[PDB]
Length: 258
Length: 302
Ligand SMILES: C[C@H](C(=O)/N=C1\C=C(C2CC2)N=N1)c1ccc(N2CCNC2=O)cc1
Image 1 (cartoon, rainbow over the protein chains, first blue to last red):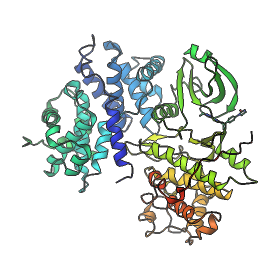
Image 2 (cartoon, rainbow over the protein chains, first blue to last red):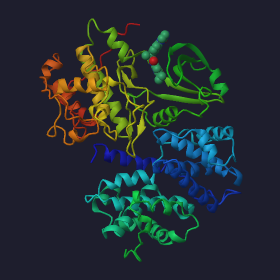
Image 3 (tube, rainbow over the protein chains, first blue to last red):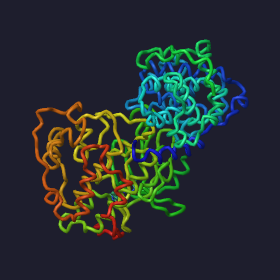
Image 4 (cartoon, protein in one colour):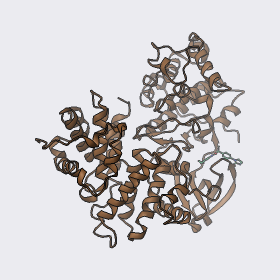
């Protein structure tokens, strides 16, 4: 357990409340929908797989996109451009060696020019005021994982899987803090794989009780159950890989007995 | 954007670099003196440089008296300007200018104290500097020292991976990195600080390696070649070789002769081989060496 563990946690909890997008920004958008967003993120998941990018990158790009759309009206035809710029910025921030812009222009099927991608990068940076170091579910899960005495790789992979699915559906996940979605994904994965529940050490650390996570836990469970029937499948496919112990194939418990 | 740039009067070039050029400048309306880091965005046509992305985003989160302050960011069409507070000198030029007399001990104590405060702030905010060397530490006439050049800094809410091309210069590189560890940790910055602390005290670099292997050997020769007892897992590291010479640990009072018991104690803890065991900046600040720290003013020959 690191020496600044608690400080960093306390701080990430502070920042996540600031980098929080407007929950109901989609109704205020005149041309795009949750569905279009889902199609966008799902696409970014594939792009992330195509260039072997870190999961954090995917998460950062989504955070950028929701913050951007929280204040900027965007038309169908430009939604992917924003997403591309977001992914590019996220790659530049998180990746050791980010893909070249030409690659990001390539993965759009020449829908946008190199010029348009770079201008959108500029606009996104302006709109986000260069605040790119946002807290993610990914980060919180990482923090939580160190309270797993019985370090279990299956639990982690499943937790990561559940967390990644939450990115696809603005409804109802936009209304949950990254630290809460992580708490729910952690418990669900722990429960499913070991039958264990949200640990006492994490209750003391986060201040979240199993009762507080219930609302988000219930939704995450339903998303897990419906995962196979979802219009978007990139995340499930990705988690069929042995790298993640094929947890997308694991069957969700029928109930949570909460 | 273009208006903000007009409010600045360029004084003189104060530095070069990969990212671009740095100028000392003055705000025409307020009279505030500043340092302008200029970045030409047409030299690579790859958008805003990753290095700038991170330096800006992480720096604007780090407001602390011992961390260089980023005052503004002006993003024109073909240029990016970062505006910083201005400081008169960097630690490397100061050490060089102090060769004859040597930086006085109380001042060395003060600088270390302040550096640990800035570094602790970084770490407790999940930021790793990763490039701590005399040249990236700024000092003013009042006695303050601040961390600067976050061109290689990284947020570690999620583990930061080691990368051959992006690493601090050899002399201040921690042993784990040299032995090929997979992930960075806050310990690499403390190691660098330890090497700097010793350099100030003795007037000579502590481990001046000519290459990666020579760097390791110089460390081994002074601190002793580490074994499994000293550093569990060391013999399993990617670049460890069973053929490494087995040197014994030199007596510390001969390594940093002018230092007292407290100083030697603090330095040895900053140079612990096992990164998990290396003292944190937070804990270093509680060390008795800083019992009587004061804030002397340097002799800045300018
Ligand atoms: C070390 C110091 C320095 O770099 N100071 C800084 C740098 C910053 C920000 C970039 C982060 N803030 N203060 C310096 C170096 C050269 C000059 N020079 C050289 C010729 N004339 C002159 O005045 C003046 C100051």
